[PDB]
Amino acid sequence: GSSGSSGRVVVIKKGSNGYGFYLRAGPEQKGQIIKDIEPGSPAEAAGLKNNDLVVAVNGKSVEALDHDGVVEMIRKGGDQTTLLVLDKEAESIYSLSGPSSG
C-alpha cells in the first residue's frame, strides 16, 4: 500500500476564481496551512478545510519547501492538482513566549 492512511487526499480543478484556497507559512511543523477558503469554490467543493496542513502535493514532498516552493508545485499541476493534508494530527502547538506586561 504505497499510500498510507495518515493523510487524506484532496482533488481540485481550476474553475473561475482559481482554486479556492490560500496558503501560509506555518510554525516549526512542516507543510503549508490553508485558509481564506472561497465559497462554492473548487477548493470547498473538493473537501478542503480551514487550517489544513499539507505535507505533499501530487505525490511530492513539499513539507520541506517554502511558501513559494509549495505554492509553485500547485501551479505545475496544471488544471487539476491533488493535495495531501493531515486530519488526525493537523493542529499545531504554539510556543509560549512573552510574559504579561503593561
Image: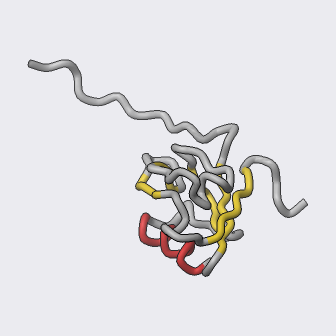
Q: Horizontal placement of 102 versus 93: left or right?
A: left
Furthest toward the left, the residue is 102
| Residue 72, percent from left and from top | 49, 75
| Coloration of the structure image | secondary structure
Query: To which quarter of the image does residue 102 belong?
Result: top left
Residue drawn at point x = 57 percent, y = 66 percent: 62
Q: Is residue 15 above or below residue 49?
A: below
| Residue 56, percent from left and from top | 64, 62
Residue drawn at point x = 66 percent, y = 54 percent: 45
| Residue 58, percent from left and from top | 68, 70
- Number of residue marks: 0
Of 95 and 3, the residue lying toward us: 3
Of 43 and 25, the residue lying toward us: 43
Residue drawn at point x = 53 percent, y = 70 percent: 16
Of 44 and 70, the residue lying toward us: 44
**Which corner quadrant holds the N terminus?**
bottom right
Query: To which quarter of the image does residue 96 belong?
Result: top left
| Residue 54, percent from left and from top | 59, 55
